[PDB]
Image (tube, rainbow over all chains, first blue to last red; front, top):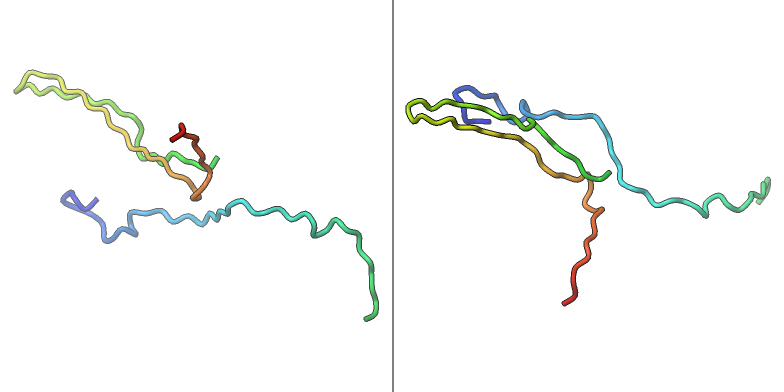
Length: 43
Length: 49
């Protein structure tokens, strides 16, 4: 606040730090695993 | 679901008697804002020209 008679040391003692992690929308993956597999045991 | 309501204090009413003035002042205060997590998610159409 930095206006009254008393106050705190720095803005860090006026903030709440959250561990919560957020992410936006991610493009869907479709072609990655629609074809069936062919196991190969050689070059 | 991309927007939020950061609010510190709600709507509060307060009554004070300024007897030196012979009034009854009424004060209403609140603290809110409108923010969004990410910098997208809105579209608006406008008239031509």
